[PDB]
Amino acid sequence: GSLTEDGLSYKEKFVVRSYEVGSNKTATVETIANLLQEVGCNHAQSVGFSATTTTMRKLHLIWVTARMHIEIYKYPAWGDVVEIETWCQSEGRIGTRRDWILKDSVTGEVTGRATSKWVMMNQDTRRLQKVSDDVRDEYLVFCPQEPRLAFPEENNRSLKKIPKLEDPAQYSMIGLKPRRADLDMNQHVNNVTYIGWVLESIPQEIVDTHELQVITLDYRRECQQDDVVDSLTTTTSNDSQFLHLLRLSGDGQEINRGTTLWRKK
Amino acid sequence: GSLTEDGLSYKEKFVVRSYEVGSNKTATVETIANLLQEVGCNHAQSVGFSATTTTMRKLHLIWVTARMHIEIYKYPAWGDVVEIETWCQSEGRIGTRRDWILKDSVTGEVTGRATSKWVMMNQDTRRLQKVSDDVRDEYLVFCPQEPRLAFPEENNRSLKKIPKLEDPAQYSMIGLKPRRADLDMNQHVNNVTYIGWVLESIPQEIVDTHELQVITLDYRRECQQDDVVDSLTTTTSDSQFLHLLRLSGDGQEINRGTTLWRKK
Ligand SMILES: CCOC(=O)NCc1ccccc1
Ligand SMILES: CCOC(=O)NCc1ccccc1
């Protein structure tokens, strides 16, 4: 992959693999989500991140995900090439945004888009805090300074407030735990695993007769390597919508909330 | 990916991804095993399986893995390229073999090698019958006919009988369930998941101080979507382990094997 001409965005091509696809022989939303992170990390490397600015490293600070939002119009087939463009933007003192555009390599038509909100956190204490002006200065030179949104629309679904699922839940999947393959290189649960866990409460019948169109996922706390998770779904609706809650079963601590939206094939 | 000049093997180059590596920033054996299955699939397509031969699809037969054996000398780093070459061979009417060699694309030096044993089964009934001369002969024209072995050496790890762990196990990890990411395009649990399930009972202190050099794994029976799996490990010894996968209730064996780890 590579930096565009202006050096303010990054593109990479991916061939969809046999094991990356579901029962339709098209890419799963967990697969899309892993390619979104691979191309993110490849952009980070390309602009010099050995992913922390100098001020970040001196204050033991990191980017962490507060929200992921993914809209898929077509899931690429087994053997197909998808093209993903990525870029970041400063959201002033609040945090940063990474956005993505997925294309069919052959047609050049937009097949997907995704937006994400990141906040600063102390790695040691886990305390959230503001982007300082020193840090802003530092990474603002890798970012288009005029707006560039994957989701421009005036009331797009990617910014909506998400409520807490009320007990009892219409569906549930109980006693979910990560294995070593769920962990990243820093031994934290991969952010994509949460997507998988949220979807495990969707009944097989919805998955067999529908196509996932939108997923909006808030991150509240992390699951540790020795935590166990309960996944809770309630239908809220030709389009099926759901509301989602992930919580630790060792006391019911909220770890993620979310909404999905599915159209019949 | 592409067939070699003679049309009798397939090579492919893979760039190791961020999420495919563990705490030392080199590929997991699960990443390696996923890459082996992708080059295998890509080879099947290249020689005209758009994987079932004629008379195979007529008597509802499929290839299923009996054994996977993997030896790693160096796990590729994050952003490195592993070049894997793969090829099949006839093992008479017993079954079929698929072999792999991995190399550092910049050095050309071998970094791993993998062998796998495959038998026929119906697919509706799942009865493990053997290779006829229609479910054969049709696939020999894609195989080197003279022997070509990732593991040539007589008396060698990859062919050894594995025994059954005796209760009580030294370590265990209980209540393992596959989620939808664990299923393939036929909604069967992907064979790579059992590898993950077997290593889950190796204690973290071992993973933190050693590197896995060898994994031998037998496949006895499939784990279904609503099955629950228990993973059991005992040191036999470098460290050596004996492994057993069994279904959480009745104690139905699904997998047995052994691993071998060198201190870093
Ligand atoms: C800098 C690399 O980070 C990403 O691109 N992250 C992608 C992602 C975020 C949230 C949930 C799942 C995936
Ligand atoms: C024909 C395509 O299948 C493969 O090559 N699969 C490779 C594999 C086998 C057993 C366990 C893990 C991986």
Image: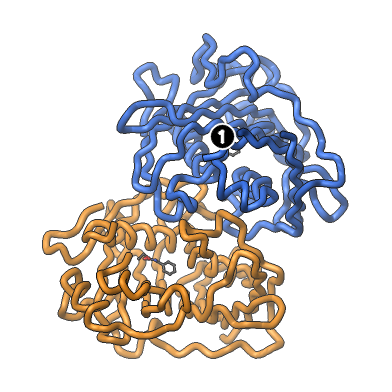
Chain colours: A blue, B orange
List the residue tagged with mark 1.
Answer: A213
Please give the name of the residue rendered at 24% of the width and 79% of the height, measured from the top-left corner.
Answer: B90
Please give the name of the residue rendered at 49% of the width and 20% of the height, measured from the top-left corner.
Answer: A142
- From the viewer's perspective, tell me whether residue B208 is left or right of residue A222: left
Is residue A64 visible to the viewer in this orientation of the structure? no
Question: What is the chain letter for disc 1?
Answer: A
- From the viewer's perspective, tell me whether residue B36 is left or right of residue B6: right
Please say if B169 is above or below A37: below
Please say if A63 is above or below B262: above
Q: Kindly indicate the quadrant of the structure image that contains residue A56.
A: top right
Front-most of A143 and A194? A194
Front-most of A239 and A62? A239
Please say if A133 is above or below B120: above
Question: Which quadrant holds the N terminus of chain A?
Answer: top left
Q: Position of residue A224 (x, y in %)?
A: 73, 52
Please give the name of the residue rendered at 54% of the width and 69% of the height, measured from the top-left corner.
Answer: B194
Front-most of B213 and A257? A257
Q: Dot 1: few (<14), some (14–19), or many (≥20) neighbours within 10 Å?
A: many
